[PDB]
Amino acid sequence: RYRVEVEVSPRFLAHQSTPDEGRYAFAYSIRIQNAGAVPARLVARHWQITDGNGRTEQVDGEGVVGEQPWLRPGEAFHYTSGVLLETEQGQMQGHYDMVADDGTEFIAPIAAFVLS
């Protein structure tokens, strides 16, 4: 009864980034699709980004970009985000906290993609 698959596609931004000064800019799009039986919404988000040097940065905010979308079964939500990286390579994994209408609590892990 609880299922949510999210897909993210990053892309290098050479026109809006200067890697020569240690400034790499990657833009990624988020695709939240609800595959559970009961409607669910995203109330919180926590990204665990780890760079090629082992150091990692954790970020915690509300549901998504300041909104708590109520994804209904079969429906999906999508928005564009922007993050900056110190190097031209890196791996980012994270999860989304969601809640069913009945109050059941559960998170939606986000697959780990790489940037190059």
Image (spheres, rainbow, N blue to C red):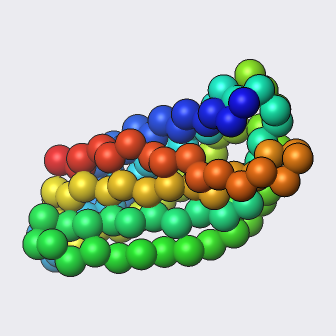
Q: Visible in this render: residue 65? A: no
Q: Visible in this render: residue 5? A: yes
Among the 4 quarters of the image, the one containing residue 63: bottom right
Please name the residue shown 66% across and 64% down the image: 44
| Left or right, 29 with reference to 71 | left
Q: Viewer-proximal residue, 101 or 91?
A: 101
User: Where residue 24 sits: x, y (%)?
Assistant: 25, 64
Q: Quadrant of the N terminus?
A: top right
User: Where residue 35 sits: x, y (%)?
Assistant: 66, 26
Q: Residue furthest top?
A: 74
User: Where residue 75 sits: x, y (%)?
Assistant: 75, 27
User: Where residue 85 sits: x, y (%)?
Assistant: 28, 67
Work out whether 46 lies above or below 1. below
Please name the residue shown 79% across and 56% down the image: 68
Q: Viewer-proximal residue, 14 or 48?
A: 48
Please name the residue shown 52% across and 66% down the image: 46
